Structure formats: C-alpha cells, structure tokens
Amino acid sequence: LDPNAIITAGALIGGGLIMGGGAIGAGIGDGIAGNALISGIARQPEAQGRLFTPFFITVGLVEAAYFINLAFMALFVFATPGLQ
Amino acid sequence: MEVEYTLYSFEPDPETLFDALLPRYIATRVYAALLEAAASES
Image (cartoon, rainbow over all chains, first blue to last red; front, side):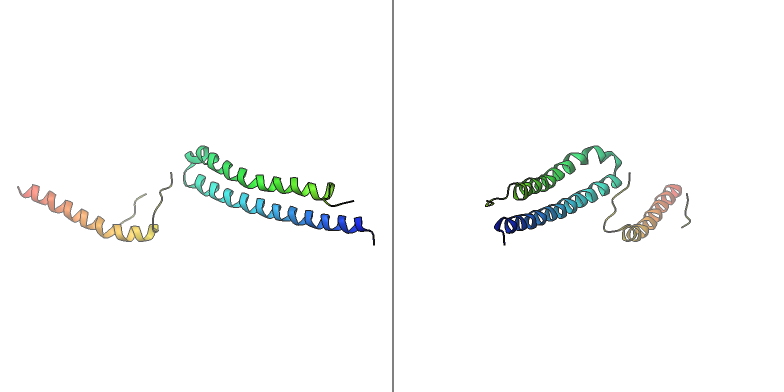
C-alpha cells in the first residue's frame, strides 16, 4: 500500500471535482448572461452595441472563477500538496 | 370595427391593453362625432 498512490488518488479526485464544478458554473453563467443578451437584442437591435459592455463584464466575473479553478486544479494534480 | 392593413414593450400583456383601449377608442370616436356635429350645427 504505497502512500504516494493514495496521495495521487486523492489529488486526482479533488481536481476532477474542481474541474466539474468550474465547468458547471461557467456553463450556467454564460448561458444565463447569453439569454439576457439575446432577449435584449431581440427587443431592440440598436442596443446590441450597448449590451456587450455589461454582458462582457458578467462573463469576466464568471469565467474568471472557472479559469481560477483550472489554475488551482493544476496545483493539486501536477504538484500535490503533502506529496512526498 | 374592420381591420385595415423596434418592438414595443406591452405590459401586462398586449391583449389586456387592447381590450382596455378598444372601449376608449369607441368613446373617443363618439366624442369626435359629437364635436364635429356641434360645429356643423353652429
């Protein structure tokens, strides 16, 4: 029963969990913001230029977290804390 | 009434607004007829 085997198993499980959670969050947030943008453009085409400014803000808040996940996720698998 | 042949935001819904507007349209046309008849009488 090698310890590093358990280390890697736990790290990979945690990384998979973070990646799945980040994917869920990014997908839902992007979909919701896109729904808002599509409805806004449908009501008035002129607003298409304007709505990008707030819409692109929201994605930035959302994607950031997702891209943070990947980052922190990369920490667990590639350089697992506590690994010997 | 016969029918003759950006997107507006109707609230609460187009149908309720139409139903409320039709009687007021008829009253407006009656009032216009009354005014024009009074002018003709004068």
